[PDB]
Image: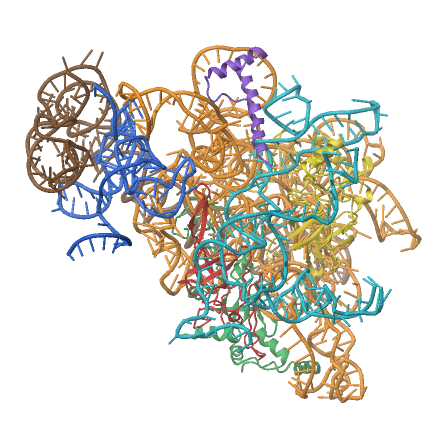
Chain colours: A green, B purple, C red, D yellow, E orange, F cyan, G blue, H brown
Amino acid sequence: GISRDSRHKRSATGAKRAQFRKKRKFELGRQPANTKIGAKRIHSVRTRGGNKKYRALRIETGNFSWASEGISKKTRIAGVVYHPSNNELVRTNTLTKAAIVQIDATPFRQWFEAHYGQTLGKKSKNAERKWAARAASAKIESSVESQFSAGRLYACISSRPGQSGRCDGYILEGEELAFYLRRLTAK
Amino acid sequence: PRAPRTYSKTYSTPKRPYESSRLDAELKLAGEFGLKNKKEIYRISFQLSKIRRAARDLLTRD
Amino acid sequence: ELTVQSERAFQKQPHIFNNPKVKTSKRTKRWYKNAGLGFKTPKTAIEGSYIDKKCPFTGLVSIRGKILTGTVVSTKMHRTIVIRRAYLHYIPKYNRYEKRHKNVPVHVSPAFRVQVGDIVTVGQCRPISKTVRFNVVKVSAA
Amino acid sequence: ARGPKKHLKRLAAPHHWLLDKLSGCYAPRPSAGPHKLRESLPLIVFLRNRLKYALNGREVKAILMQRHVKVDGKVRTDTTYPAGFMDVITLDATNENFRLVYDVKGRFAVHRITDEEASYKLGKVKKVQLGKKGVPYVVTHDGRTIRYPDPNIKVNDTVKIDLASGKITDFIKFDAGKLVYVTGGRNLGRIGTIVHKERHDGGFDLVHIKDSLDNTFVTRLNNVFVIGEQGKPYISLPKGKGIKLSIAEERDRRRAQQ
RNA sequence: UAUCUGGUUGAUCCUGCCAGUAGUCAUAUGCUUGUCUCAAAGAUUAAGCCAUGCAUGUCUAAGUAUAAGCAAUUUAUACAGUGAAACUGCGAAUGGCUCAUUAAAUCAGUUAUCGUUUAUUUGAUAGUUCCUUUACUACAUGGUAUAACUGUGGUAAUUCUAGAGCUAAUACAUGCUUAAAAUCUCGACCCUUUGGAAGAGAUGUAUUUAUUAGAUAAAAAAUCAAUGUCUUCGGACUCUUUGAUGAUUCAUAAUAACUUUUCGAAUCGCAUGGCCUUGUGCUGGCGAUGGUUCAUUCAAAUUUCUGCCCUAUCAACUUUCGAUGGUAGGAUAGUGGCCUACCAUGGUUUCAACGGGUAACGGGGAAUAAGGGUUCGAUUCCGGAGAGGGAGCCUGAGAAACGGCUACC
RNA sequence: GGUCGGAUUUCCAACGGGGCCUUUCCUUCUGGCUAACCUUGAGCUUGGCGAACCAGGACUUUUACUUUGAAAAAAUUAGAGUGUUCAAAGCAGGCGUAUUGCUCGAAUAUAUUAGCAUGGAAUAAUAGAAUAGGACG
RNA sequence: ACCCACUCGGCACCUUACGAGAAAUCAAAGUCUUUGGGUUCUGGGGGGAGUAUGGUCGCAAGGCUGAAACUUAAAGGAAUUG
RNA sequence: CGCCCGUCGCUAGUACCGAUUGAAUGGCUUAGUGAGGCCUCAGGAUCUGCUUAGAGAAGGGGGCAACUCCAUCUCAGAGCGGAGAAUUUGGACAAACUUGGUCAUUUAGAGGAACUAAAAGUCGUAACAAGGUUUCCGUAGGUGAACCUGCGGAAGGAUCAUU
């Protein structure tokens, strides 16, 4: 099986180590997950000590946080558009960590309307008072406004689905948002 | 696996074997004290030598 | 050292959420930590725009265990160097010693500016790489 | 070797049990428990080689199974349970209560005591932490884990316990000038009345310690064991009280008690 | 117990070696051998091949028993005694054998896990499980085999197995049943606008993500975005609370969601105890079993400094296709070139790298001695490796298992 | 000898140790201890300069060396005691009023280098402020 | 250019033998069993053998490095008398 | 009449060179084939829960007469699903084999050239005295053999000596 040690590697001087042990179970590795989109499939594997490990596959939907609002909603995923590690993962649309994807943006939109009563893109006394108090925060910024206009919003995957069965992440904002859209636009 | 029983002798052979003086003296001793074995004689001399080494390396000390 | 976000990824300190909505003083935030044992987190690390997560101060890499001192001899690597531990192994039979050296490599932050000959002490941290275990905490030259 | 050990030879078993290098080439392995392997006394070696109340492990299992015995207020019907440091054992037969403490000769003594001196014990705090749901707790040197103690109770302190519950009768903090007991090193069994200490921040907090003959020494702060305050011990102490007289002084002692 | 002797010469002094001499838990052999006690023993050559037979199975009071097994319940109509076989649960990863491998590798001392798993024991630990949450649902408790067995049997042979009929569970798949408050939302409604509002859903545990708190060198001043506490609405403003750590994004707590859904006892033996609202009502003990989390203990894996025999008739070595580092990601139980994508081109070297050899596993130790030392150390204890050579993997907490499977030789 | 060959005093002296001054700061700021308190109340009173306890801010140029300690698994080795009938061994044994029973033991030493702390500062090197980016300021 | 005296550095010399060494002999071949100022290079009985091989240099002749098997009790140094 | 050198000749041994594209053994290994498991794309025998599903027509309840209500053995047919082996794509792991290369460890061998040893072998007599041409060192040549000769060097020389 896939080893995880350096008794099969070279020393630092340039010296082939000798053959010392047989491969183990506590120095092993396993194949990547290569998590994809559509028709959620999660095979599980038994690990060292029970200690289950949800090998993600074909994951269609995931969770995404907006930290300026402190909220965290469930959403589908349009597809990945950029990965620093490999344009191949970008092309083949394989979800991993640090992964730049597009999501529906509709739950965030409708929540914004329900919470502030302030439009995006383009009543009762209690809710009116609520929105009047929650005002001065419907001014997020131009790029997110455009992305809510488009209905496809840029998020970063921060989970490890092949280890967790969970595509979780957060919407991009401001600095890294500008950095990554610049990377996309680089032509 | 059973820890092995210690064994250690109680004698020591002569350094140099054939010295007529040594042999006749220890023969006198054997023939007066009724002994059979230079083994026994060496054994007693070895005990004496052990205690004498102790005496030396003790009176060396303050 | 022209650009902190030189690489394709977005290098930063994790979890340090600089809220773009509030516009407060010190536009960007920075975590840090006193390493302990009488060490100092330098002001270049405090004011630094850099990231270098493998640093003990701004990063998340606890120093703990053995400590060593040596002189730097290499600088040709990226946030990593090699030192020389000149010491003397004793021989009881001949009752006298012999020079030996072991060139351990260490990790270095942007918090230090190191030229060759700068004597330096480090701290045992976790395995930074195949070759490395230690990280520099004080320099002793100019 | 591919998994946990199960056996134990003699001569890997510790010294202070005084197990003999003859009599079969295998030894009683202390099964896991609230105490370590080495600073622990199995009940088999206890009953079979301290009292001679039995001769063979078969007899000892008969005893443990008929339940004349009980540790921590519980029967503890295992032949190789770790009777560790300070611990209490109560025997209906003879209405005895033996306590497990050390002697200066580096051995687990046999301290005959009464039922109330059994009904309380001592325990060194090993650490303190905050459990889930905001329940502060601590854990002792005998695997006992206890909740909602005084915040004044901090690390290296010692507690005196009810033995019907794991709750506290009282506690004693660590500071300069308190009576202690030693566990580890050449000083196994000493009682030496803390005089001062030293930090060396980074490892090995050390303590300078001397018993009432002015005789001083130095020990590790995790090997010491604080038993209360200077003068009064919270328990009764064995022959010697941790003194370590000379070979010749002890020779003269026994020659007076010929 | 810091010891010498014979031998080159016709003789002498010397160098210089030889032989002699003493010992060995160092072996073999020879010749001989009456006794007591202790005891090594197919390592050296072949880690060469192996017939035959054993070497790990296992139950209580207490998981499942109608053995068409055996005693007798007669205190028991369901058994309730014992009890093969079988299901189940544990363990079979320890022991034991050998030393082939292996020369910075194991190992020995010495550090760390602020970088991780951990059955088992031991100490603590699951009011929150009705999910259109009102009929959607037994909780004095729910569903399913299936074995054993009955018999049909099939191969020359196998711890070979099919076919048909039963039946059990701590085996499987499921499953409700106990407080109180407290914030959010809504939000009926009043409408007020200083703005007041009934009523409704949530909150246990666990996983994953994002966010906040998790602290605290020193004292006054100017206001307000709007006075905020209560008002003399002149403003008095205090009150404030946070543990450990050498040091943490630590322990730990809360907001918002995620979960294909984790745990929250349908188990078992004894003893039968108390209230009367006189109901098989309600409550009750000593236990065993298992069970989420944390800690502990026996472990385990990685890890810091130092240290290894002979060789230069081995001086350049490493990097194609990982060698040195870095970023991102994957995998791992976990860090990390462990692996990949991309990138800089570095890294070790006469202070002997690298390569070769080793009748080399290492150490604790053994013989031997004035000291210094030399030699040996497979070999009873410690750590490693292996099961005919290699590779792989299932089960499991734990194996790369070999008295377990798959293949090749 | 004040004990009948034990132990004490002024002890003259030596021996090594701690401290002050001799141009000899041999880190100081915050603190509480304010300490040693100049603080004195009549002969035992009310108030001195922070390490002597401690938390820190602080300069802490580098080593080798050397001392002490913790620690270094047992067995082994040396070695205490011990009548396995002696002995090799082993760690047992011994004593009773032998009915209740009593009772010392299973020491101690060694443990290389390397690693931690550690008093020292001789010895050996070791940078220091010179077309002063020099310290006190 | 000579003489005298002195001086530093050189090639060496005469005598002693305190000292050394196995002896011849030696102003170092001394200040070494009362064993240590600093450093380099080489030898470990005689032969085999400065052979064989492998590298390496040279046109070559040959050189530098350079073993083993096997054999043997002596070879050898300095002096004495014959 | 001492000691002694070498060739040649006999006997025995040890190692070396050596054609033999020598032979074996083991290790590392390019390339190629590449099993076998494991993961992933599908697969779908098979079993199986739910939802209806209409009727061949029994039973009883009701217009008691056609007719009507529901259960019923029945069988399609339909979806809603659960598990699902054989087989299967691709991937990493990668035994073994073939072939070369390479590294070391032993080994056969016609013959050739050496060395050593061995009571009395032949040829001479090079060496030790000025050894009968003083010896030796290096180099070159010569010849049956020791060995000779030339060029330079030394004294271990047969001289420490010519004012």
**Camera-nearest residue between C109 and B60:** B60
**Camera-nearest residue between D182 and A154:** D182
Residue C125 position, x and y percent, is 52, 58
**Camera-nearest residue between D212 and A60:** D212
Q: As displayed, is residue E216 above or below residue H44? A: below
Q: Residue at x 63, y 34 (%)?
A: D27
Residue C121 visible somewhere in the drawing: yes
On-image quarter of the N terminus of chain D: top right
**Camera-nearest residue between E405 and C1:** C1
Residue D82 visible somewhere in the drawing: no
Which of the 4 image quadrants contains residue D152?
Answer: bottom right
Q: As displayed, is residue H11 above or below residue C128? A: above
Picture mark count? 0
On-image quarter of the C terminus of chain D: top right
* Left or right: E118, with C108 as reference point: right
Residue D128 position, x and y percent, is 69, 56
Which of the 4 image quadrants contains residue E247?
Answer: bottom right
Residue E82 position, x and y percent, is 74, 31
Residue A113 position, x and y percent, is 61, 79
